[PDB]
Amino acid sequence: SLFELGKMILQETGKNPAKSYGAYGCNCGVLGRGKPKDATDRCCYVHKCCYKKLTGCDPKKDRYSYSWKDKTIVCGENNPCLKELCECDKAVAICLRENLGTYNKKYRYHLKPFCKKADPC
Image: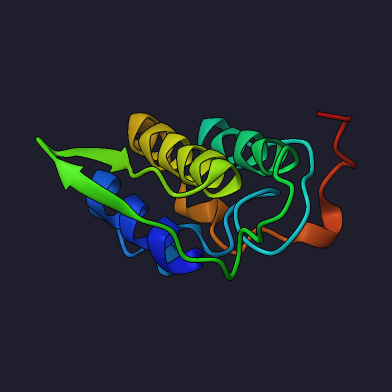
């Protein structure tokens, strides 16, 4: 759910997730994709495409288990959908941390109404 996802982004990046990524560019935040504005935004574009494989679980509401071991996110077994959900969330948290070097506050509440329509995943 958003709780695990938010916690992973905070563990990897050290940033408040909602403030930094709740509404960044064309893909981080409220729903839908759009052409990405930069590398951070493209992490979120990839994360929303990753959610498309899920069947039987809901990425916003469903909780799942994971732990922090040797400063690494480790998804627990869960069930098949929840395990895929946990790995989609872990990958976006890692990708946001890898791209913090180009993060641009000017994209923070970017105007989603103006985003180019996203290509198919």
